Image (tube, rainbow, N blue to C red; front, side):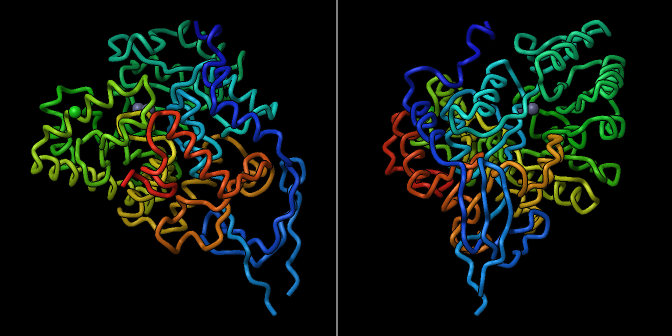
Amino acid sequence: AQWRHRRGLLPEGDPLVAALERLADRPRTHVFKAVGLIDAATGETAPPRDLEVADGVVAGWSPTPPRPAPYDWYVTPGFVDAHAHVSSVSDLVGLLVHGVTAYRQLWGEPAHLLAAGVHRARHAVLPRPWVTAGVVDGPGSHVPQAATIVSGMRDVAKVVDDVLGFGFDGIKVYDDVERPVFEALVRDADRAGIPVVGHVPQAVRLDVALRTMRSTEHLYGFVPNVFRLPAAERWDALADALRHHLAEAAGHFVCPTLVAWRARTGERRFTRPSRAVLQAATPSRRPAWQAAARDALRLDPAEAERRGALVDRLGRIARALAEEGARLLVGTDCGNPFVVAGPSFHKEIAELTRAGLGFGAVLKAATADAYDVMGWHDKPAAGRADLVFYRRHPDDGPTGLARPDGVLVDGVFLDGEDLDRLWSLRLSAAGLDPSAWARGALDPP
Ligand SMILES: [Cl-]
Ligand SMILES: [Zn+2]
Ligand SMILES: [Zn+2]
């Protein structure tokens, strides 16, 4: 049914789709005066230059004439959510409003390729996807319904056929892929130029996974995927793993999704489960989110504190990996309970900076290194005009990067009132009064 429903992210008659279609009729040619381009690696700002955008491509920079000219704008490359589960147009709007102009879809379907076609066609304003061919897992998978079960070379070949035939961007592996099958998959994907991402399989050595996979997610491998265990043992098992706990990761892309770990604990300090966030969830997600809310309500505060401390340690592991030369990415697992597409991206920046990552490092993870892991080798602020605009430097002020004053998406400029209106519509469509969740707040106050 994946072909019949391939337009499922952009359903006819939907008000959010209609808004994104109207926005795609906007001009894609601009001049922005006195722009300070923030260097995606260092966080320093180039001198003020006038930015020329032509048909959605960065055409050039003209020095702003002096009296040294002040900055009218500070600009970053567009952000990349390196681990998103986009299932509805609500998610697409949430990402755009928060400056996320591209995402890795780590459970890809034909519907995401369709969305990529809409992006190429300029028929709606939306973030650009990087799409896996579903997810590959072994027999004994914990997700056998949703996973493509691979147990030999012919099964591996069929996945490579789908990737190369339909233009998927990579292959995602799950925990129960058998070791001989993994070895054949990474050998054959490598020969075909296909990146392999996902979970370090239980049957695979960490060092082998680090040198063969384009990226590894959730810190699995460094720590166990305790969510494969019964609920009552999970956090004890994580505590034990950390009790017994990097330079092998130098140069490798690591997407820790700390915001998702935090939300799975049932803690409330940073995840802030609430009736308002449940109202904002899409109808298909509300049952699972409500069940998670019940778990959070029932959790003894002392245990919540214990689990939060374990996720803090995961963040320090992510920092230590970066200090050894690993290449961190900012991904959210948005769609998981109380991980909201858009704000969760900035929650993950907050997790990484709480762990000690500086502004420049987290900006590089949000942008330049994500374009590299996706194989998009235009310079981060060149080629397609995907950029985020701020009237004040985003390393100052209360919202950081989370409240752009503009987002340029393939040349369409969404100004602050456009961003307010899109966010308000995203909330109203889900049944939440927009005044309950001002743009720039990461949770409804
Ligand atoms: Cl409840
Ligand atoms: Zn995962
Ligand atoms: Zn995921």
